[PDB]
Image (cartoon, rainbow over all chains, first blue to last red; front, side, top):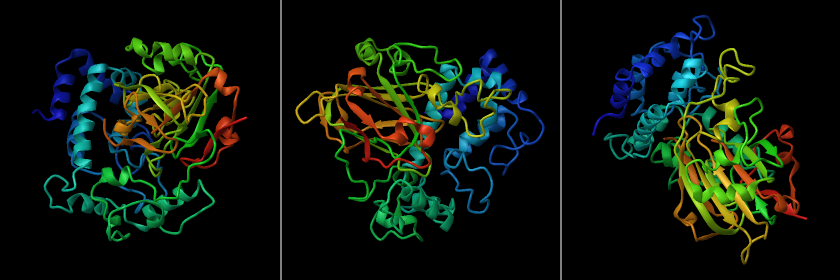
Length: 381
Length: 41
């Protein structure tokens, strides 16, 4: 019944170590430009946890702002991520890294971001009429030429069959136009929008892309467990798949030793649902609690690739081992399958896009078909 | 957001991944969902 921001305030203030860290993670941000402003450069950087909490509570009833409409030339890495904007530089401090690895902090963040998700799913925008959720999107700038062109261009960049208008690409409610932001009832429906039929045809190949996504890494001959904290972040199957806390996945870890890991990134202006990469029978499915704003030391202040203006962007391999995430293991050695053994699909949250939503067609024992929509990321915890 | 796909050693012997995925530094755009990622050889 308690406001989850208030629960977080109490956690910070009633624990001497967390109280210390919640000061030091701001004190360790340099005073000097550019760190006097957040990474968008549009606002002064937050310098204390009470202002942070005030803003977190305010954000519970806000959709992300498309700030590029009036500010087209500022850094755009954090479009969609209002909480991330506040803590991005603190995430890059030594005390901030410790703070955002604390399991109690992350339970509190989970509850805050899930309360946020309740608002983002609410077509009334918390009691502002049946169009409140839609109007919030328009007020936030998402029906601007800049936003809509960005969404259309991003969808077109991955195909030769380019479409001129948003409505030819994505499904949206009836009578939708740019002026009414396609009548999307709330942020969540916009965020998890589906492609129109035929816009993403399923390829004949045995393996298809599970996400509309940008290749990041391809690693061969991966180890059972590895030093994922060292530079370059070697993948650690045991940690990534959660064998730490579920012995039932341990046999799948063993079966992936020597295998390959492919990783790819979903931008804020990309399609966010998940499609089945192969045909087969689901043999294992899990959700794993973890971090939200944990990034590497290399991505922080004084780091060899830091501080990241959009953490955990440059830490994507690292967070596969600790972030809120999910695991799906598909057996393709079945009738209708490609007979390429077991295939794993591990969606991994980043910051406040960390709700891993498995659809019911992925229940263990069901067969999925290549190209079927099987889940989605949502803004949330 | 980010995601991994994981393949077994013996399966990778049988598969040809597209270059944009196997050599990610060459990629300049999203890959289209449902489009080819790897084919049997």
